[PDB]
Length: 279
Ligand SMILES: [Ca+2]
Image 1: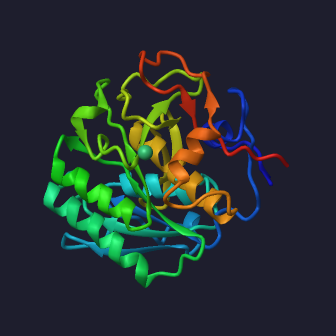
Image 2 (image 1 turned 45 degrees about the vertical axis):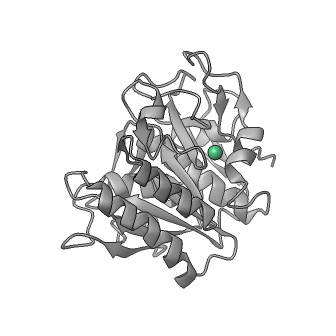
């Protein structure tokens, strides 16, 4: 399948070169997989989700996304126009308030929630969790991310936006999950992206168009935007049978475009997520 005039990040992850605008992907499109977006919520009524998104948990007075961030991330995973995996099932877990903030104890609870809740959902092709959030190092937060991964969920986490070594942020620094840095449309590391040996992969993160609350769209930047590209890619590859939750981060790194990014500090991987789709 081909989607013309796609957002640049979708085109980039199906391409060996920058500068194109068509997204190529297998029609299966993540059908039968599930992606949890652990964030500010998801505006499930947005036409772009087509009934495939549901809020399943909140830790606040409402499950509504009053911010937009979680809706944007969910859109990059799985909206019809702006998403990688256009037929996946999206589940929202609201661990961040409408200001985009959350206590670590609530974030931990949300991760352990997903490890259990996947047993309440039909996801025959596999389960992914996308965590576009983080803060300073916490062993308890890292341990929760490790548990979620251990339980059979592909965990993708944002590296962070301090232009610093990600070893000092959580859950970015947990080795067993898939830590995602951000790139721009000219294959430069995004200027804010964290780096370091704990990164596993880069994805598009500067000027990413996706869904927003109020039935709208907008373009924003962050490692928060790169992470759902990798989460959606994992769901897509799991539906195709190419990998599993335990193996997907390694598979994505093995099949990535190599050596194509600029301003990669020495010691950080030079790997850009790629779907290897050949029509
Ligand atoms: Ca890993």
